[PDB]
Length: 211
Image (cartoon, rainbow, N blue to C red; front, top):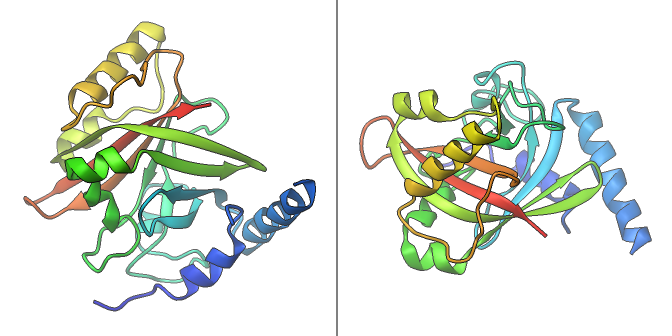
């Protein structure tokens, strides 16, 4: 299938993930992204995949299923962070994208369901507010979309509630990541897409911030 890929890869040359003078380069990258679309928040890259995108945040979790980075009507849409996320505060950053079965957007999240892949490809890199951060994937799973929509949280009452959430997300994983010391001080990143193994499948990857 052929789709809206070309513009959303013009942008890839604007990636802040290509010294204080390169840093300078990456800052003008972010400023140009923000200027193209003020909804821009950060850049995501996933090791070993073609996931290498700008991430936006809309006013709801539907706009950017159907619009591109320029806000034009689009089938591929955009990669977007949950509209309810507070990126300064929240312990779980939740990010969505399409899997339209033509190897674009978040299609390649499905590769993490293969144990060899999961073992070999550990890291998700973000670039936000002039800073690179790394997250190590510890959970991969799929389930029905309605259950997922009820389970995924960005906001926690207290530490105990968060620890409980972390334990749930880790317990769900097809595969165990050894030595990841998952704990309630951690900050996590959740990546969500659709799958086609069963109707209304969602595929989920959860990763914790390291370094």
